[PDB]
Structures are given as C-alpha cells and as structure tokens.
Length: 150
Length: 71
Ligand code: SF4
Ligand code: SF4
Image 1 (cartoon, each protein chain N blue to C red):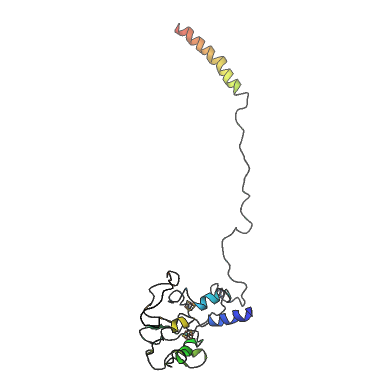
Image 2 (tube, rainbow over the protein chains, first blue to last red):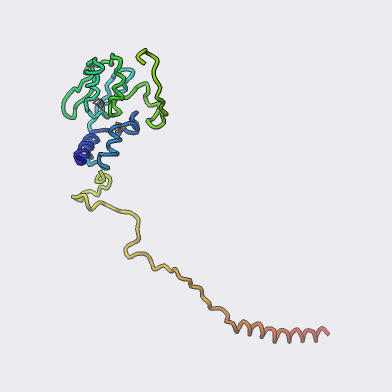
C-alpha cells in the first residue's frame, strides 16, 4: 500500500509544475500535504514536464491548469452538484485539459466552491487572487447573512 | 534529479558523481602540537642568586669605594 501511494504521488508530481511558491493554495494543498506525508521524499523525473495554458473561467475562479492533476473532481462537481455542465476533461493522455472547450465563464453560481473541491491550486479564487496565505488567516466559524439559507 | 545537478560528462552510472567538497589533503595535515612546551632554559636557582650575591659582593665594595672618594 505504501509503495503504491508513493508511486502515484510521484506520477502526480511528475508533470506537475513547481508552482507551489506562486500557487495561491500553497499551504492548504492536498498534493503538498500528501507528498509531505505519504509520497516519496525525492522525484526521479528530470525531463520536460507538460504545461497547459490558463483557461478563462470568469472573474471568480483563477485557473492555472498546468498545476491541475486532472483528477476530474471539478468536472464532476459542475456536472452534478452545481448542475450547470460547463467544465469538461477535453482530450486524452497527459494532454488532458480541464475546463470549458469554448471560452465560457462559469455562469453558474455555486461554482466558486470548485476551489474548495479542487485538491490542487489550479482552480483558485480570483478575488482572493494572492492576497494571503493558508497560515496567516485566522479563522472564525461565523455564519452567513447574504441569503436566508444561513 | 541529483544526477542533473552533479553532471560530470559521461560517467555511465549514478555512482562516480563528482563529489568535490572540502577536507584534509591526501595524507592529512601536519602533526599538530597540543602539549605544553614551556622551555625552562633560563638562569637556574644558582647563577641567579650568585649573580645577585656577586653583584652585592662587588657592587657594595664599589659603594664603599665611592663613599671613600666622596669623603
Ligand atoms: S497544488 Fe500548488 S501548492 Fe500544491 S503541490 Fe501543486 S503547485 Fe504546489
Ligand atoms: S478539481 Fe482541480 S485538480 Fe481536479 S481535475 Fe479539476 S482543476 Fe484539475
């Protein structure tokens, strides 16, 4: 089991760009916290990682699909929970790219939660562009008052 | 990585990596002294008393002769 986990966390960090310093979700990252806990301490891949252009997904979700690991979590969230069906896993192989095939802002509300859904920095809040870090933020378990769902 | 940081053109293998870091030269350094080499080659117990006593024996005679000249 541990060798299988290390194997996979090497593949994920293989074509993944070294964007952790410039990644908005640098501290709060499943990939960083699984590599620093279950993945191997070193990487043997020394070649040309694949890179992906940044899709325009609107004024909410800043997208850096190079970081994205193509786990498909968001393309499932938009199809099922958000129910708008705009995101897609275009292409096959390493060339897999997540996002709308035509430039299409995620017109759906409830589609800003894809950032919390995303286990990787790729999909991040564009309003919270880089303004802070996962460790600076003091958290209060407040409620919301915008809409009456509370 | 670690085979793209320490290149050494060729080398056919992950071993034989350059590995040039600081250390003693081949054959170590010189034998360094650590003991207390305090040389006691000074005037002995005598030769210091006999220089002082000799100075007293002759120099006080000279004080006497100078007192005779002054008188
Ligand atoms: S998601 Fe961002 S912070 Fe996490 S490993 Fe990838 S580049 Fe680094
Ligand atoms: S949730 Fe994030 S990491 Fe997963 S496929 Fe979508 S963009 Fe890529």
